[PDB]
Structures are given as structure tokens and as C-alpha cells.
Amino acid sequence: LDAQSPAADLVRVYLNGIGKTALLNAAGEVELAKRIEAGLYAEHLLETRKRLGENRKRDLAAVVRDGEAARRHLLEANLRLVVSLAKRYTGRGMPLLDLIQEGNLGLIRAMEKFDYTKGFKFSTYATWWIRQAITRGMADQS
Amino acid sequence: LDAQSPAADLVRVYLNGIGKTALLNAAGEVELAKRIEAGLYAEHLLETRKRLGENRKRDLAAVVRDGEAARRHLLEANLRLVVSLAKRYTGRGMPLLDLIQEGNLGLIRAMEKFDYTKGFKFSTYATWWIRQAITRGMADQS
Amino acid sequence: THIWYFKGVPSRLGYLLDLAPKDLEKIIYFAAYVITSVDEEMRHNELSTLEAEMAVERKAVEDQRDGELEARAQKLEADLAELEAEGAKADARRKVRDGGEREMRQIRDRAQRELDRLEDIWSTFTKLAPKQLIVDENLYRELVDRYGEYFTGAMGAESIQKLIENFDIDAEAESLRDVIRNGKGQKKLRALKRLKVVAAFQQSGNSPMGMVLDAVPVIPPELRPMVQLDGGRFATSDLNDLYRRVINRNNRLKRLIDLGAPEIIVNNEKRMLQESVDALFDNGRRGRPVTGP
Amino acid sequence: GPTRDWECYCGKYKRVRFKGIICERCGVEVTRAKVRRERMGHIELAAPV
Ligand SMILES: [Zn+2]
């Protein structure tokens, strides 16, 4: 066939891609981040006590895999928030895609260098970091 | 030091070794044996579809380990029964140790070639096989 | 092992291997494991790393127990607040409070069970050296699970064989001579006895490995004459009976190991074989003597 | 050494359970602030003196 078809909006593709997100209500995020911490500690100990041949030789690798999986979801957790904050700062000439991408970069730079430290909802911290990142993007765009 | 001490009865050592047993009341044994079946099926498929490189490449090995663990407990399940049946056929000159050992051999020969096949309590089957084995032992002793 | 030694007074093995008779007999008849060799220098290099790995794991159990304590304490406080809101009698208040307090005491005690197990594991790990004993199988199971890397320890006669063959005599002889050169009569007499035994071993030009057998011989058939009665019954010296028992049990061991089976049955069977050999080399030396007629 | 104790420059390994681990992201070590008191630096000269 050779019939033509209409194009698709880029934003709608983003919404379809993130529709699978399901926020954890800020409650379970602490254990979510305890999975990352233990994963990194597994990283270190895997290459520190190397000689040990044991059934545990696979459990820590599973903890590292759990840490890799725990981040893949934590990042999904905040895309609604980042898109909202980005949309809050539109109308300055930039396509919403460029701002939301910049906020995505800011988020990934944040949470991966964040600790609960008996801190408050990480959502406030993410909002702050992504807001700073998008503000910097707009400023450098001029 | 060089003070002397009394010896220990062999039977009491057996009782101490088997005191950790905890029968499952004939209810969960079916799944217990479904762990062995799946383990053997993992055995076969591990060396039949070898090329596949996947995260599942470790799950079946875990199923084989689960099958190895599921048998180590199933065998523990029946030692009280075998010792009882052996003690039921004493007084014919044989040490109870030799009879109980023979019954242990008969049991291991049984359950590892047994299928539920919607069968009754496996305890009856084990009692039958160990009784036959000990009877054969006594007969060959003469 | 040869019954004439681990049961003799003095027990040559006990003096040579500096083990109490209780420990030696537990090892022989498969009662309590033993630690053979340990690469202590290899453990030392990462002793700090091991201790750090301990700090993090013990802090992890600390965090889980603290979380459980916090959760249960908050639950009990909420229950007490609810009961006060309902205006119930102080009897219900004390019932709920005692239940919760006992629950938290149990939780903390289980946490302490885990912690004391962990420090026992450590203690036995750090202050670990040959000739040490572990009565309880569960603790050894745990040790080999958490740290199965450095120390290799097995149970049975082969354990003693490996220990003695790996062991050296001249160094112990020199150490005992040095101890004797000092005073302290109380320990000096024990040092004298052990030095006498070790010096006899050294002068003999032999090796202690003769105390663990792998091939018992059998006397000719005439020495154990075989007799036929009016009905041809076997009523000759029971030496045939004892050899029958030993051979039969060895063949059962061989068949069982060929068939494959868990450690419990194999160890029990090895114990039975050791019992039979001890009986054949001597009946009634220790324990109930075998009696057929 | 680190200005604070058990603190990488970039925050990658800020947790307490890191000793002897140099952070590749920032190239610093994780030890108490005291170590800052016992390490030295050498300047390189382009002309002997
Ligand atoms: Zn860093």
C-alpha cells in the first residue's frame, strides 16, 4: 500500500511512554533507595573480597541487579512532576521538549547524588534541582 | 588433661541427628515433589536449549538447586517412620543399626523412583518399600 | 583408626595430638567437627576488610531490628491512644501494654540472639587455630556458609590423618624441650610426658600415619578353623562372624556411595564401619561387647 | 582530603560505610577529616634552587 497518514505529536509520544508510571506516594521510596545503597555496597564488596567461593557469590550480584532495577523505577517515579514544572515555565520561546529534556537531565543528576539522611520527601529536592536546571537552560539560551 | 570419659550409644547419635526433623503432615509433600520434577526438567532443558543467553539462564539453575534442597528435606521427613518399622522387626539377632541402615537404603531407592500420580500418602509406599528391604536383609542374613 | 590407641591409657593419640579423650572420641565416632588448616596470614591481610564487612552487616541487622522496634512501639502507642479514646478500664490498658512490651522484649531478645550469634561467629573466626573443636553442627554449618573460604574442617578419621600428616614433630619436640628447660612443675610434668612420646616417635624413624588404617589383614583360614557339625552347621570361631560383619558393612558403604545420598546417612554408615573394626580388633574394649549366643 | 568526614566531593559515596574507596567521579578518598591534617603537597620547580 502507499496511502499517506498524519504525523504524531512528540509530546503525545512522551505521555504514552510515561503512562505506565505509578507513583509510590512518597512512602516506600526510602526502601527503594535502600536497594540502591545496598547495590552499591555489593558493587564494592564484590571486587574487594574476590577469593570467596560460596553460594553467596550470586546473592550480591542479585542485590546489584535489584539496585539497577530499583533505580529504573525510581526515575520513572518523577516524570510527571518534572513535566509539570517544565510546563510551568513555558512561553519564553523554547519548545517544551527542550525544557523537559533539560529537566530530565537535571533529575538524573540529582537523585543519583541524593541520600535520605532522614530528609523530607525527595519530591521537593527533585523539584528544586530540576527547577534550577531549567532556569539555567533558559538563562543560557538568552 | 588425660581424664577418661564414657562412650556414647550409636542409637542416641542417630536420635540427635534426626531431632531436627519436622514432618509436613502429608499435605505439602505434593508440591515438595513438584520441586523435584521441575528440577529434573530444568536439568534436561539446561543441556538441551544451551545457546540461549538470558537472565533466565540462572533461574533454571536455581530450580535445580531448589530440587536438590527439596529432596534433602523430603528424605529427612521419613526417618522416624523407617526407624519405627525397623524396631518393629527386631529380636532376630541383628543389631538395630544394620536393619535401620538397610531401611534407609530402601527408602532412598524408593522415593527417588516414586511419583504422586494422584497417589495416596507416600508414607504408605515408603513403609511398604522399607519393610520389603528389611525383610530381604533378614532373609539373606539367615 | 586403631582401637588400641584412641582408647588406650595413656591414649597415644591424645598425647601426640594434645587432645582430650572426650574430643578425640567425639571426632572418631562422628560427633563434633574439627578445624584442620587455616591460612591465617591470608585472613590477616583482609582482617580489617572482614571487620568492616562485619560492621555493615551488624549495622544492617541493627537497622532491621530498630525498624521493627519502631513499628511495634508506634503500633502499641496508637493502640493505647485508641483505648484511652474509647475510655476503657485500666485493666485493658495494662493488658495491651504488657502484651506490647513483651512483644518488644521478644523482638529485642531475638535481635540479641542474632547479634550474639554474629559475635560468636566472629570470635571463633578470629581466634581460630588448629586442634580447636566445634561441638554444635549448626554453628559450623553457619561458619562454613558465611566464611567457607579460609579454614577447611572435616569430621572422621581422615580428618585426623590429614592433621597428623600435615603436623610436624621436630618443632613440637623443640618447644617441649624449651618448656622443660623452665620450671612450673604442674605443666612441666605434662610437657615431660608429651616430649617423651614425641621423642619416641622421632627416634623410631617411623611416621604417626600408622595409627590410621586403610587395609586390615585377615589371618589364614586354618587359624580360624571352619567346622562342620552333623548338620554341617557353622559353629567354629566367630572370627568368621566378625569378618562377615566388616566385609558386609564395607560393601554396603561402597554401594551407597555409588548410589549417592546425603551426608547424614554416609556419616552414620562410616561410624558403623568404625564400630565394627574396633570390635574386631577387640571386643569389649569400650562399650557394650557384641553377643550373639 | 575531604573537607568533611566520610564525604566525597560529588556525593557519590557519601555514606558512612566507605573506607579506602577513592571516588572515580571526583577522584577523592573517604576518611575522617583528621587525615586532612597529615597529608602534604609538593610543588614542582622549573628551575633548581
Ligand atoms: Zn565523589
Image (cartoon, coloured by chain):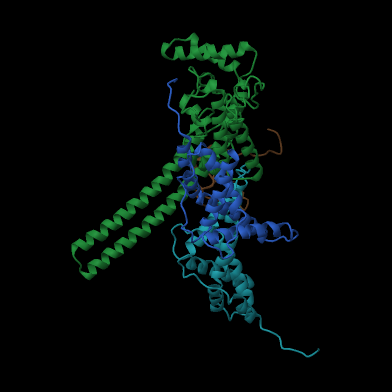
Chain colours: A cyan, B blue, C green, D brown
Residue B94 in percent (x, y) is at 52, 37
In front of the other: A88 or C221: C221
User: In the picture, residue D10 is in which quadrant?
Assistant: bottom right
Looking at the image, which residue is at 50% across and 39% down?
B92
B50 w.r.t. A142: above or below: above
User: In what quadrant of the picture does the N terminus of chain C appear?
Assistant: top right
In front of the other: D46 or C265: C265
Is residue A32 at least partly visible in the picture? yes
C35 w.r.t. A98: above or below: above
Looking at the image, which residue is at 46% across and 70% down?
A25
In front of the other: D19 or C167: C167
Q: Residue furthest front?
A: C230
Q: Residue furthest bottom?
A: A3
Is residue D5 at least partly visible in the picture? no
In front of the other: C147 or C220: C220
Looking at the image, which residue is at 50% across and 8% down?
C181
C95 w.r.t. C174: above or below: below
Looking at the image, which residue is at 45% across and 50% down?
C61
In the picture, measured across the screen, residue C83 lies left or right of residue C224, that is: left
Residue C267 in percent (x, y) is at 56, 38
